[PDB]
Image (cartoon, coloured by chain):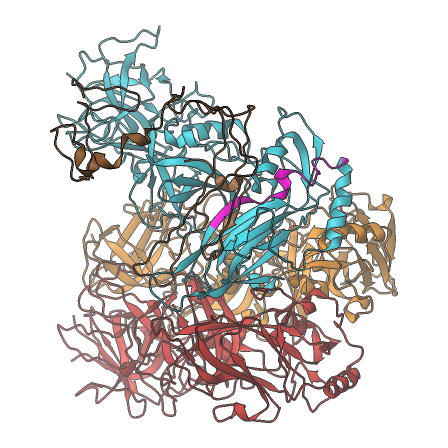
Chain colours: A cyan, B brown, C red, D orange
Amino acid sequence: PGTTTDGMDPGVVATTSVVTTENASTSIATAGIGGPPQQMDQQETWRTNFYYNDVFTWSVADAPGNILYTVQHSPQNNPFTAVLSQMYAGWAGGMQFRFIVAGSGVFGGRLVAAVIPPGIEIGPGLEVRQFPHVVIDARSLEPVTITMPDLRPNMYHPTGNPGLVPTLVLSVYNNLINPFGGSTSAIQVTVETRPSEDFEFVMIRAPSSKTVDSISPADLLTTPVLTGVGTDNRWNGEIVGLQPVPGGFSTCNRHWNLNGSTYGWSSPRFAAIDHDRGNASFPNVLELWYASAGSAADNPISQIAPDGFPDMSFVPFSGITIPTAGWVGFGGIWNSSNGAPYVTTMQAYELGFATGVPSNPQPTTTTSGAQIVAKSIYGVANGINQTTAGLFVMASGVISTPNSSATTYTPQPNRIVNAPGTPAAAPIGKNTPIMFASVVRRTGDINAEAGSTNGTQYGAGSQPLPVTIGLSLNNYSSALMPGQFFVWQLNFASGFMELGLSVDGYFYAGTGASATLIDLSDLVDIRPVGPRPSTSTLVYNL
Amino acid sequence: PGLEVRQFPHVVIDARSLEPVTITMPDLRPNMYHPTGNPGLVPTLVLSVYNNLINPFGGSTSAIQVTVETRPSEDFEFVMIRAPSSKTVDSISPADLLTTPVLTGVGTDNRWNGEIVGLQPVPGGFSTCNRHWNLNGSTYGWSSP
Amino acid sequence: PGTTTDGMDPGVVATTSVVTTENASTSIATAGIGGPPQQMDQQETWRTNFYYNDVFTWSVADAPGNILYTVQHSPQNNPFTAVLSQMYAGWAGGMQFRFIVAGSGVFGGRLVAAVIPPGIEIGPGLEVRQFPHVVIDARSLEPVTITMPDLRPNMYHPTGNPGLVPTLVLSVYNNLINPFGGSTSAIQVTVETRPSEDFEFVMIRAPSSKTVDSISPADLLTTPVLTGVGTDNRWNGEIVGLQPVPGGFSTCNRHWNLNGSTYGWSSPRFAAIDHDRGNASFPNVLELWYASAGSAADNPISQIAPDGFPDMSFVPFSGITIPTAGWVGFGGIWNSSNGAPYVTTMQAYELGFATGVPSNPQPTTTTSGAQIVAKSIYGVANGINQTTAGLFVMASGVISTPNSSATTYTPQPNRIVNAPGTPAAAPIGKNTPIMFASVVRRTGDINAEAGSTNGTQYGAGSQPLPVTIGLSLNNYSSALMPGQFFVWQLNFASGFMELGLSVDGYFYAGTGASATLIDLSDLVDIRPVGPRPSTSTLVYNL
Amino acid sequence: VTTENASTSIATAGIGGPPQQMDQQETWRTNFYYNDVFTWSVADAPGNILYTVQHSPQNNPFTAVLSQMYAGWAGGMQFRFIVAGSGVFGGRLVAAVIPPGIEIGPGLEVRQFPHVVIDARSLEPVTITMPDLRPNMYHPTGNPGLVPTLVLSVYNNLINPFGGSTSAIQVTVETRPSEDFEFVMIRAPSSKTVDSISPADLLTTPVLTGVGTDNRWNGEIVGLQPVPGGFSTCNRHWNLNGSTYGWSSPRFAAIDHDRGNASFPNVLELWYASAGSAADNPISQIAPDGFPDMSFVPFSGITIPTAGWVGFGGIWNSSNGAPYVTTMQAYELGFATGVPSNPQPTTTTSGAQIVAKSIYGVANGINQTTAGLFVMASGVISTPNSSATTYTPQPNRIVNAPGTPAAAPIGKNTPIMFASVVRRTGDINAEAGSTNGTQYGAGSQPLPVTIGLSLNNYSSALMPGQFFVWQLNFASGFMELGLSVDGYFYAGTGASATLIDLSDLVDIRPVGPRPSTSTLVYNL
């Protein structure tokens, strides 16, 4: 019966014009520069069965020619070839894909598939129906299997740096049609994989040896990073949610990219902020410290500001009323002659960026022509006037607030200070940049964590700290071409969604225009998917 | 939750199946036999949704039923007769805790000592400690049953 | 199985009386006058596979005899023969057409196909069902292939002018039926092609050489014309939408037809408006200027009006009233004797056609017997009385409005002035003519552009300017017969629609009685289709 | 026509399937066809390089056409050289094929590679073959990889014993494929490849025959004006990397700014604002989109500024967007410094202020601390009399932004500007040929070229130090025009300064790339 499918059954074998005997024979001949092939026993359980890769949705609103699914050729597309690549230096050959369509006998509609050769851009203007292709009906009962050959300009694929490869695309041929109309408007398709008969590894290597270029940043984002261990890269607090930003934003301090560089002035850690010379005065009085941005000689990362200095905008205040949504830190003033601290100046201070603070303090979001200012939000015991004086504050802060209430998430996009030349994160179609949210203490109610009737206060950061560390230590320069994401699937008990990482280090979600926070308390596991075009909408099925 | 069944060797079954489909579960064990008192390591069978069920008419009909039946395979056997009243090292199953007459007019509740005649859902939730035992044989209350 | 269709499979081969061996042998024998046949290698991948040509829609409202799809025999009906036709000067042979119907088992209805010999007029009135023909059911699962042979009276077809060729027609045989009623009332059909075994090219030529017959108009409308680069032909503003006009309208100024002719008085550009002899008076004051239509002696295009004068009717006003929906330009008065401007008459004016001006100014829409009037809308520093004075105004105008609010699109169809002999654009079946919309500045609030709180103001023109320039530089009379459109397809992110253009220069869409404005920001690309009969309904799947 | 590595090339190209388009008797394969021309003068020293091309299918018209429908290629090409010299000339050239990994530059020892030798008096053509010496199994069309180069350079310098007007000759190049050339893997003709397209279609006959307009005054182009001293222009100007340094988009529409200072302390209204504060503008923050890039001209009283940029508009209320109806006049606009107390012109955007002063008395003046400006961006030229003056702007009047590249003469190749007819205030009725003279404006690019450059990236079409050359054929005579990677146009007029009239232009055809140190033909 066609209603039952075993684990080794390919179903219907469909061929396009790219599968020829020349390609297979040439592949096997030229792979011989690396010696005899390894792991070729064709009777092993890891090689004869099909194993799961993905599942996608076909809706009645998808127009003809719209792309539904793409995959780039790699040994990372099968769970066991990925494990076995940890002990070899090269690979070659192709891989089979099995599609199962979960339709019914009354539906109508057709799909189409083709193999796209290297050097061609994958995007909405790609005309699949003008390549050699196969057409598949929506009523198909048996599985349909399609083979992607190894079309490569190299003799073999180096494990770290493979080079050009082909890709497989599936799109809509004719619209899915339901003759009854009504509420049922979509079906699902599942994809599985197994290696072709010419797949092979070459040249054994010690598992502890390091390839020159890393294969994939899949290991950075694992389940504990978002389920209770990782903390954000601005406030150092427990990540509990994802905040979309429909407008766009930019961030450079303690933010690394995939070329192993930062534009900021901080390290991936939280420590003490120390600068040796500043201006102190008090014209229960408020102390006032500042210096000129761009003269931090002790910092080898960047001469812009002392390591750990927050990248928010100073909000002015005076008299009685204390400021709002400022960055608060603990410490005081110390003498720069011997290092002793002036013991009477200890308080909580509000730190930030500003311009012209001797005469008129105006917030600025630029690092050029600005100055860095610290002001005590409360009165000190005994103030000090000095010409040269140091500063000492911790890197973990809280949020100033006048009353017991809570405000929006801090900081807001226009409050972030950036250096000249920093790339920005902007929407691409329905995909929107996001920030990572963590609950942060505030000075208006110092016993509120979660469930508090006074409200919940959130602090947002651009990257999880373990990701920032991993990007600062390794080099991922060859994993992503421009215009691609690296995608993970986030599984919940009720729904799932996808996260994309760009070459500039910003994370993305397919939220469109919504601005509500997404909660992570019911997350189960995280699974990697691999490179995909950034024009393709990221799934959001929560 | 977290076990990816679709990345083990597996079988797929359609919702339109007319004839029955039979699957065999073999005895993969690290010991020479299973004591009924404590059997040790055994394998597990799992059945799970592969693709969502669909009714093209919509409407009020939104579920179907599946029936399961069993019979032993040809290598199944027993050994070592014992007394029917003997107890085991591992705990007796809790299936006997709730028989028919417990809820059909013989059993009583544990706060008022009154004949139970219905079940009350509590969507909000609640907690209780007095005269309440857990499955580890312990209580946090101050009263005897 | 029947649910999978490969790229080389024709499916059911259905034949008619016109496909014979005598024709194929004679075609191959007589094509030899051109030399040895080129590109006739039977094993090449561009010949063995079918590739995409078109998709059309079959609806339950189509009556028997309605034509759904028709093409003249030509190399432009396959993409690779379209490519190769660029470098050859002659061709001969036939072509196969493969149809795939996207239905299901519950539908009913039939279609009919026939090959019409050359020399027979194609149009409404041709009874296709009284030629040899083939009938196809709406429940078909496998594809059906039909061959169109090369019946010609000459020894080969020159690419410059091919002469007589046959035509393929597909038409409704019995109405489509859905037994459930409901919202599902249409299905799709896909068309693919490949050359037949006697098809050949002859006589290599330079790729840049032109032909005796006119170039096809497909290049007149490329993607960037409507995606933020092209401008309209009345206000010179970036087109951002399409406005249907169910009532109809007519236009002559700056409007060309497909025979390379215009009835207006203006050149396809935007430069200053200049006339030398008119009356001037002002009985801070409003200044009046006017002349008699039919006296533009220095304009070689026509004598009706100076080159660049607007074609909108005049709204009279006096004193404290600022008119609504007037064309407004900036300029002043100058002395005709030495060409110097009266420097105190510079202001914003309003221009239009009128009659009985100095006594009882009334709006008009006929150029015969009218006057051309300009009047300042605000008070100038000092007025002037002259019995002969000239006019100079810039030709990129704005729309007057008394409040900060926005009015409807201007000009409304009944404010347009037309010279005698101008044809009209009336709805054809369900096909309705459209204008091209753009944002125009208004004097009520000069800072508003788009998405304002006070509102968005729209202008409208009959053609895009690049299209008008292309029609002015060429003659397209041999590309389109009367009763025909040239059709493009517009693909959006979600949905698609088709657009038509007639021999008189108007564009049409299949909107029906709808009057909503269609936005163009989410448009992906534009693809040409070809000539189609004007009674065929243009698809509107948005 | 064979190669010495044919069997290996064909065998290893089989990773992409069976070869396509390899029928050996097809007419497109058997004939030579035109590819390019270049020039050889008496001033070129031995070792100077005159012609270089990388191995690709773009070097033959029909392989160029065929590559639209394929995704890969392999094999070599044959080349042919045709010297247009005479019997009284004397000199030799040398040509060789350079393998990948060797630096190509001046002084390279072509004479010590295997080579052919070409005489200046040669009548029969001379041929050479380029095999496909590649380290990959095949070249993808969108990303080919490493390829060899063909190089031609001077062996013995050209001599002219008669010594007169003639000092250069031309050489024509034709190509056809070798026996082992092939294509692989069909693709859709509309699909996109990484490599850039050619720029030959940017310049066609209508652009200069009466349809095109220049990128500063939006006027119809009628002539070309050389600038022997050089100049630099940034606004509405794109390079071959798809970038600009100015603050404007390739379009003409009204100029608008929200906040600024206005005063009249029948009066002459004055509006000014500071540079670097155009917040709404997404191209640049220097100035509003469309503000002219010319220096300001101070004036007062009855004086009317000469050679000034003038537009039409007035002030408006920033609170609700309503205009002040009594301030409709003609204003002069530009860049200046010290604007309130002592206005002086500047030719830089750093620390300047944009100014808008009316040249005629307004209906009634306005005093406001904050106000807005609205002016149409197609402007005219202010003159105090009926007569015409020199073309505007002169190069000493053009505002530029820091880091903008300049254009300087190279040998006898001189940068040019494209000229259009502009109306003037003193005589607003004179158009062209009038008895009071003809006023000419000038710009740096034709607008269709600017739009095409802003829509696509041409970074792989022209390496630095090369021009792209077009033919300009007149009724009597012809000349050539060159385009550089910084966007400027060049002609071979040397020290001449007279305008060149395009009334009798007939056709424009593309020629090909050429080194910028070579001579461009001027036979008019």
Residue A48, magenta (yes or no): yes
Query: For residue A500, which quarter of the picture?
Result: top left
- Nearer the observer, A115 or C251: A115
Q: Is residue A170 above or below residue B116?
A: below
What x and y, as percent, mark residue D151? 78, 51
Residue D96, magenta (yes or no): no
Report the span colored magenta: A35-55
Query: For residue D184, which quarter of the picture?
Result: bottom right
What x and y, as percent, mark residue D152? 79, 52
- Nearer the observer, D99 or C243: C243
What x and y, as percent, mark residue C362? 20, 86
- Nearer the observer, D188 or D496: D188
Query: For residue D24, which quarter of the picture?
Result: bottom right
Tell me: C255 left or right of A373.
right
Give the mark count.
0
Quadrant for the N terminus of chain D, please. bottom right
Residue D475 visible in image: yes
Q: Is residue D255 above or below residue C394?
A: above
Quadrant for the C terminus of chain D, please. bottom right
Residue C388 visible in image: no
- Nearer the observer, C176 or D90: C176
Q: Is residue D130 above or below residue C322?
A: above
Tell me: D43 left or right of C483.
right
Q: Residue at x 45, y 30 (%)?
A: A468
What x and y, as percent, mark residue A332? 27, 15
